[PDB]
Image: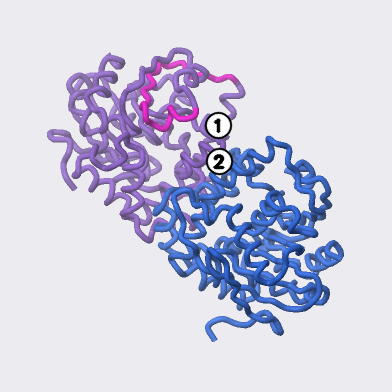
Chain colours: A blue, B purple
Amino acid sequence: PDLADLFPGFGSEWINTSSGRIFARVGGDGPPLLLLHGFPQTHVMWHRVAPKLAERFKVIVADLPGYGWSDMPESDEQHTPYTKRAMAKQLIEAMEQLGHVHFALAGHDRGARVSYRLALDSPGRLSKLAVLDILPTYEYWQRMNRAYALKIYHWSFLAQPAPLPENLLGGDPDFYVKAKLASWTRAGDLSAFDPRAVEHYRIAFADPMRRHVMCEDYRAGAYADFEHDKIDVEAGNKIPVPMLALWGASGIAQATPLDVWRKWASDVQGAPIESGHFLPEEAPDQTAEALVRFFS
Amino acid sequence: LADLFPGFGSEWINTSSGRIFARVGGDGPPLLLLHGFPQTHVMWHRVAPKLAERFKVIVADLPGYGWSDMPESDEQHTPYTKRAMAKQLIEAMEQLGHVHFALAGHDRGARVSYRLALDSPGRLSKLAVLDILPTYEYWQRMNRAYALKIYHWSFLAQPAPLPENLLGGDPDFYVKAKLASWTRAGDLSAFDPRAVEHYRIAFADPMRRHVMCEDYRAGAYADFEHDKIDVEAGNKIPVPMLALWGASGIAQSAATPLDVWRKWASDVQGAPIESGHFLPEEAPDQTAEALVRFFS
């Protein structure tokens, strides 16, 4: 009706946590694998590659806390419930509700930031980890110069104190969500996306409280998340989980991503994928292929 | 609109690139006063009568701002480059018979002023800049802290129509937020309400707002390139210069202004004034005195 079912055969589950419920589409069977979405999308971003992974895994496609259909915990002045640290702990809680204490994880964009923070804080919870088209938060801010500030302007814009970004995004929320989706594709338009998927992103972005939380996300990314990343880099903490790093040839991560990730993880492999930023939709077959071989 | 320059004449000056509006008053040596973002010529209403004591004061709207004509921009935003702005105002000065004049600039017009002195030093007797550093110096010092501080440099520079769409939802809010955020008090209490209505009305026009985005686009590309050639070639400004910066201004953040300006000019004097970014309005008496003593 209002929104289409893009996960045929997948169940729909509401997982209870201390900080609120998390929505997830669960399907398949086998070892548990968690797939997290990013900005400005929802879990439906995984609809093209989830069926392939469901052949070998129990795939759980969850809304990040405050995103999609997940509950939105009340934020505070340090934006703690939307830090990557607190997000990871909520997701660990949700997984325990499912009986999964040791699972595999793949993240994209904001949820990818949740993924590597989770691996930094709780390595024992992960068998293997994959991040798609990101570099660590500390690494983004440290390389901030003229060229990169123009490219990822929204990192500083979205981090402005409330209610300035909330008011401006309300000027034309339809346009902004579509401008962000097309600008990061290799094609430079919406042709790569499925029309039913864009309608999910459109509806979610249309709610003023949803946009507030995504602002809280980027505010955490400019302050608290930077400090936590800053502690680890100074301490020499590296990720012990076997890791795969996939980036788009015209993505945002393009520093040399693999050389950068070697400083943050003991055991990491990497491959470029011919796409823009949205790998699972731009290059679904190639993304699914790299994930299954790594996770198997 | 209120008359904030009592007794001043009003002249419409014709140039190749369009007409320039200016309020003319006093008598004596000619002195040009330029405004900046997001204001108009009326920003000078507190100090213009004092300088009109001793100079022929010309208070002009920048090209595309206020009541001046708005030439059509192009792919490089050429008519809103500081280089092209400088030639237009030189053209307007010649209309009045002023081929050798004194100039003081604030914010964007200060950028026009130091560009004017680099390209055409012989046209200036003395030059004053208020609460700025060269454009190149802003971008070179861009880091995490500064990118959060002056986010609008990267936001306003995004390709059209992305900022124009966001500003159009509630332009009243944005113009007031920018004026209040840059004062030391952090509100609109420093400004005269009749002057604020001038800024609001000017910002209320969609074509005006496009021109200010074109200004920041030139400041993000062409004007930086112009600054880059001069800084690397060792070209310095030979005109005697005065640099006034606010203790809570933008220039004082992330640099010490006087040492920076010594790198760009042979003969510079500088003084800090206890104010925010809007010197002629926040601290009118202290600013006017410093201007009169320097220009005399």
Q: Looking at the image, which is closer to me, A187 or A37?
A: A37
Q: How many marks?
A: 2
Q: Looking at the image, which is closer to me, A226 or B7?
A: A226
Q: What stretch is highlighted in magenta?
A: B234-254
Quadrant of residue A280 within the rendered picture: bottom right
Residue A235 in the image: state x and y as whole percent.
70, 36
Quadrant of residue B130 within the rendered picture: top left
The residue singled out by tag 2 in the image is B221
Residue A209 in the image: state x and y as whole percent.
44, 65
Closer to the chain start, of discs 2 and 1, is 1
Q: How crowded is mark 1: few (under 14 residues within 10 Å), some or many (20 or more)?
A: some
Amino acid type of the residue that numbered disc 2 sits on in the rendered structure: Tyr
Horizontal relation, residue A33 to residue B29: left or right:
right
Tell us which disc is closer to us: 2 or 1. Answer: 1
Residue reaching furthest to the bottom: A1
The chain containing the residue under callout 2 comes to B
The residue singled out by tag 1 in the image is B141
Horizontal relation, residue A15 to residue A71: left or right:
right
- Magenta segment's dominant SS is loop
The chain containing the residue under callout 1 comes to B
Q: Based on the picture, tell me whether residue B230 belongs to the magenta stretch.
A: no
Horizontal relation, residue B104 to residue B23: left or right:
right
Is the residue A253 above or below the residue A172 in the image?
above
Q: Residue at x 55, y 35 (%)?
A: B142
Residue B53 in the image: state x and y as whole percent.
17, 21
Q: Residue at x 35, y 23 (%)?
A: B99
Is the residue A120 above or below the residue A93 in the image?
above
